[PDB]
Amino acid sequence: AVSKKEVLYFLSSKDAESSTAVKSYLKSLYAGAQVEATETDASELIAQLEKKYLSAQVVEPGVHNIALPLGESGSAPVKRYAAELFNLGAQAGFECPFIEVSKKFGQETATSETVKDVLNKTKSYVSADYNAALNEVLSSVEAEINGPVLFDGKTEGFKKFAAKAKAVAVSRGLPADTILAYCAGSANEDAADKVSKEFFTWFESAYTADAAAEVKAIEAEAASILDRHLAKPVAQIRKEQASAYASLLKRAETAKGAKWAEKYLEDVKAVQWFDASVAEAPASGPKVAA
Amino acid sequence: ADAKALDELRKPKFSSKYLIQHVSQKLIPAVKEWEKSYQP
Amino acid sequence: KEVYCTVITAEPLDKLERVELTKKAEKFVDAGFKLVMQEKIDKKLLGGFVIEFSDRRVDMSTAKKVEEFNNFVNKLVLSI
Amino acid sequence: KAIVDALKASAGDLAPAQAVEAAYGLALSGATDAEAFKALFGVVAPAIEKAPDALEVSSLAQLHVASTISGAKLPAAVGSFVAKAFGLAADAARLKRSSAESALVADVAAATAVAFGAQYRPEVASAVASYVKTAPDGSVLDIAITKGDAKVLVQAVPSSLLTSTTPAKPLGHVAAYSKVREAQGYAVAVVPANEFEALPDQKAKAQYVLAAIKKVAPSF
Figure 1 (cartoon, rainbow over the protein chains, first blue to last red):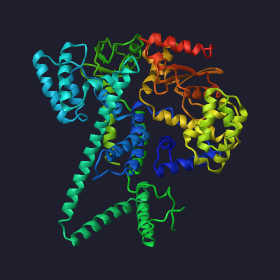
Figure 2: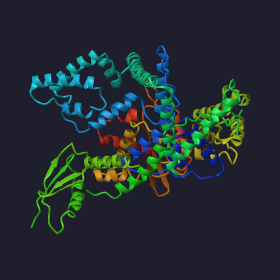
Figure 3: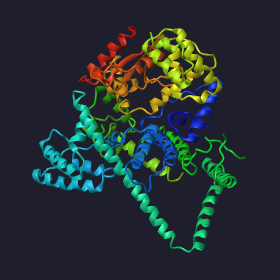
Figure 4: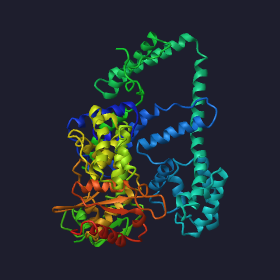
């Protein structure tokens, strides 16, 4: 059963095993069961850890339900794949990726006075091809002041760095004037409309190029896994795979009583139903209850 | 036997979801007993 | 028969942030000894306080509660 | 008056997920034609009685708003069931809170602590933890104040629940959440963030919150 904080996370979720846990919970509440009071407890560090591990139970069956657009031509399979992961972010409680990674910046650098310590605590989230181009330009503005460039904004020594880092950001290809004019806004709704149409033209060309770089790495991983496997004789392949299949079954049979190992071996019985339901009618496929 | 369902057949099979649940069922109740008992 | 101290906080204190701070500190000396006190500020602390007794330190900052939290969960998920 | 009487005769053409959003939209606009709500609730009530899991929990909560503001009743198994599903669908929007709404609620609750008398930070931090009482349906209210027999709820409605135009009044769903809580014993004081965060300091934000509580229940 679910712990009533999982089932609040699975309401806007749309995978199968989470909706049938919701639907049997809503069928219990139709038969007069009391909805248990959700906890007004679990302080700021424990609340961010439950949100970390309940979002990952919405993301994990959702990622396995998104077909990769491997070996497709065009942007719309890559835009479908990116839109399904956007919607998986919203179903799991994430915001927009722009609003969720900039929250990661301002959280990791809450205590930063100099921008060299910004550029070292946001190292995991910024590309090293871009972290280096902001560190080389930093040491030139460090050469003009011969004092550490501050994370102040009011400082004029930062204002000449922010005009040099804007020259770096346009060199990568990303419009730093359009990005800044979106998250700041404007007064009228007509001049803010044209900059949102120009941010979302960058943003869609941004997240497509992250999805397409993810597809081009799965395509390159699968093509090197296959070409290594096609160089084996077929007798080696069948026993390398039967050794890997049997070792991975035994790890789920060593684990007794665990919920994951009970569900692992129950899905092995559901794959063998799929192979057996196809053998009865192969022009029809698997037989669904209809 | 035959003809399972549709909502039984829409489940992704070898996802984690239950290692993530088994970890959070043994990390969240084990860390509430860390902040309630914490002095440096 | 004093005990000299210094307290580092994140922002300058209220007059009630001061009084409930000393009762945290009168139980970190094992006598009826008075802390005189000394006040410093560090935005690198995320709130809380750091008392330096000039021979020992008690770090009840939340900037250190965060670090001891992550090191507890980053080591607990590696065993489970 | 010509939409609602078009809806009372042809409420058999609507799916139960569509009849909910008809009755929810009439209740939010202030319709009292209760026989239009007899027609709309005549679709959704046998549909929940056949399969209660047929509708979304977001739509079972939009039924409880519609079954409250117009006041038209449901069956005894249905109207008690959709009352829990307002408590479910309001918690799920609180766990998945936008984190600038979490920055606004903890800002409004701090100004609610200053308005009710707290000069120092150990008093506002111990007061906003006392504002997080539990609603009767099982959900959690963030700024819920109780003085004896009168309760006052403070509601912060950030920008996602605001109209996207320049006057920027809050959307109709904020009066949905208000009038359901008002039928639970609360006096919902709306604090919108287009007015709240234009204020420069914490004292002006506390008198804005205090004036908003006086306008709704002047006992506080």
